Amino acid sequence: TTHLVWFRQDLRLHDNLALAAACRNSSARVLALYIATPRQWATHNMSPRQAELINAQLNGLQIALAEKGIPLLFREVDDFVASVEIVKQVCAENSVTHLFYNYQYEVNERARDVEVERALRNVVCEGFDDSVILPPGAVMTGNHEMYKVFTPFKNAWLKRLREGMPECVAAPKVRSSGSIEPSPSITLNYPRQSFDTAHFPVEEKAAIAQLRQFCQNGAGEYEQQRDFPAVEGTSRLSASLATGGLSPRQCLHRLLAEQPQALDGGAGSVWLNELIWREFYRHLITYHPSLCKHRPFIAWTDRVQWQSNPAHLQAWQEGKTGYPIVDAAMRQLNSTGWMHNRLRMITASFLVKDLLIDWREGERYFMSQLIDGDLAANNGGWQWAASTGTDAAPYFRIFNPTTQGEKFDHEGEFIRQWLPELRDVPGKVVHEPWKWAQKAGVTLDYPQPIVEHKEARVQTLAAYEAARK
Ligand SMILES: Cc1cc2nc3c(=O)[nH]c(=O)nc-3n(C[C@@H](O)[C@H](O)[C@@H](O)COP(=O)(O)OP(=O)(O)OC[C@H]3O[C@@H](n4cnc5c(N)ncnc54)[C@H](O)[C@@H]3O)c2cc1C
Ligand SMILES: Nc1nc(=O)c2c([nH]1)NC[C@@H]1CN(c3ccc(C(=O)N[C@@H](CCC(=O)O)C(=O)O)cc3)CN21
Image (cartoon, rainbow, N blue to C red):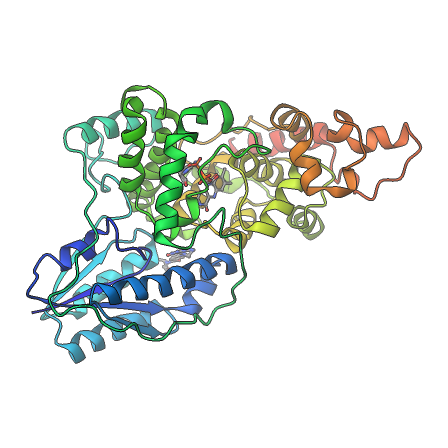
């Protein structure tokens, strides 16, 4: 009996469904496989910082698997089509009787998995819904359709959660054969860049410690602090969650352990709501695959006449729009691979609704930079800002970057952190530095608004209006 565990976006020993399931049979030979697909990653616009996070978790996992007496067979092919052949070869070469793997919901990943299952004729394959707390299809509407509005989805989700809460499975124990010697460190052949390991922990114990600490302190204050970018009021666990360094059940159980009432509206319930948004978006692409194929959820939005303007898109990408809160947000992204949620909303809105540039442009750019890049969450957030998605912002909802900035970064603390050239404009005017610049006969080394919000807004409303006709 030989059990093969095919890792992907789940590089952890703890609470890993396919892994725990392969090791139940203590008399079975257990092998782990990991296939690097540098070319499919490039196509999917994988961020260099995330590629680096994965590489780091991959070496740390190899080391942890060795102590459990489980060996990792590393392979590097080009794409998902090639991987099918590699899984076939590894099964054949090692006489694998059973394959255990955790499901991936994106169109390309699913197609690969379906091919692997068809190809493995004499093998028993068991996939697991490890990336979600509740599996797609667990929370369905009365006519067995997926929910289209979050509010009722959430209600039904909490209901089913209560009828049987999934539990955290433990890290497997050492194999009968004993510990083994780790193979030499792997190096992913994909452009990679560094990141703050303090904010985004690469080690499993560090990820867990960060979840612990947040749930103890942060989850209670969350509702009151989550809106301020200048404040560290969010978990910064999105990178671990996106790559599989942590599972959503670890977050759930650790949350309820510190905030008991989180399930019933008490403290910690607002943070839980966000984990339910994550759930929503993952089930949604599972039932609506076209969301993985650049299609909007609201068909008529495809009729909006987006602006083809290279100068405007470039200014947004480089953070030279002339709107401090938008610019500071882009420098944050470009330099750390992460952006505060409030700012992901503001910058995405600025691109689609002030510049009227196709949301797919902003999405791709975000993916290319985001250490937490994830199709369901990114596509979902972009379709929300653009009013093209499921339960998205209403088309007439056009965030005003100055108002947004005055609210959430009233003092310009965050702003002055990322825009050193504005570290002399006094407090309030910092949100509209050029208006003050003239009235002081001063030259700022900062751009001027590339668009006037009032007129931009009018033009956009007209465009949507015309498409919605
Ligand atoms: C245009 C846009 C693009 C986005 N791109 C991504 C992306 O690629 N990857 C990603 O993980 N999130 C994305 N989101 C949500 C995003 O803001 C992040 O979740 C991030 O801010 C989390 O930082 P945190 O870990 O400190 O979050 P916390 O606030 O501490 O939230 C905890 C966990 O819940 C999940 N979460 C939080 N907000 C959302 C959400 N609205 N939808 C789904 N899950 C959520 C994340 O897995 C997160 O780690 C996007 C939002 C917008 C508006
Ligand atoms: N991580 C990840 N996984 C993905 O699967 C995925 C991404 N990211 N990023 C975007 C790409 C592109 N995706 C796509 C885009 C188009 C088709 C597509 O046009 N396929 C049609 C073709 C039919 C025809 O040839 O007429 C289909 O119906 O299968 C499929 C997947 C999904 N993709």
